[PDB]
Each structure stands twice: as C-alpha cells, then as structure tokens.
Image 1 (cartoon, rainbow, N blue to C red):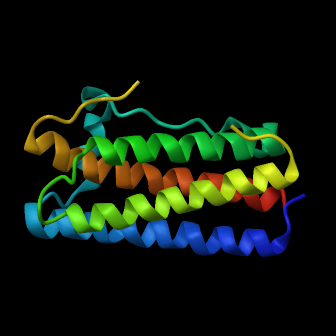
Image 2 (image 1 turned 90 degrees about the vertical axis):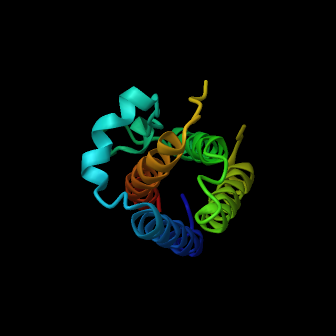
Length: 158
C-alpha cells in the first residue's frame, strides 16, 4: 500500500537520523567520555526513559494505520525527550538541534502520507549534568533501534 518512492525517501530519512545519532554518541564520548552505551543502558528505568511501542509494525500483528500511527507517535515522544535534555551541554547543543530537525521533518512526512492514505492524529526531567549527558546517549541508542523496527514494518507494507 505504500509506494516504493515513499519507501526510498523513508530509507533516506531514517539513515540521516541514524548518522545524527552516531555523531551525537561520538561527541558525548569525545567531550564528556561517556563511551560505553551498553553500560549506560542499564540505567534507563532509574532515569525514567520510556520506550515507544511498535506492536502494529511487527509481522505478527502488522496493520497499516496502526504501524504508521505508532511510528508517528513514537517520533513525537523522541522530539519531547530531546527537548527535555536542554542541549545537554554547549559542546553538544548544535548536534542535538540537527537531530531534532531531522526527527521532526520525518515525523511530518509520515503524517502527510497518512493523510493521503486515510486518518492521522508524561515526561522525565533531566536535571543534572550527568542526567542530561547519559540521557543523550540512551535516547540516541533507543531511537536507532526504534527506527530499525519501524523501517522493517514499513518494508512489509510496501
């Protein structure tokens, strides 16, 4: 139901967000020496970082409106979480603004496709420097994986 031209634009946009997330983590390691995301992942629940559901994009319970709607809802959660980091630090802030623009640009394209197809439409605080810097490497990590799953769901509906 999704045209291949749309799928290739989605590929382009998810690879762009992934490259942004990669640079964010490089920079957090370089500037602030947070260089092991597997160690930090153990702290997500302590920091209250939520995960966005994509059950409608799994092959078992694939649904076109549901998958697309959950990808859009998920991308707004990540907009909100990036916004909650407040730049992380003067060294990371430019990299965060590019990620924020690329996430939001993609989320708008999804809404418009849902409109041309049929019908589209809570937060942790990060108060200390450590909370903001560790929040930055976990959100980038979670967003990478969330996009892999969403893209698999998208492929299936092509």
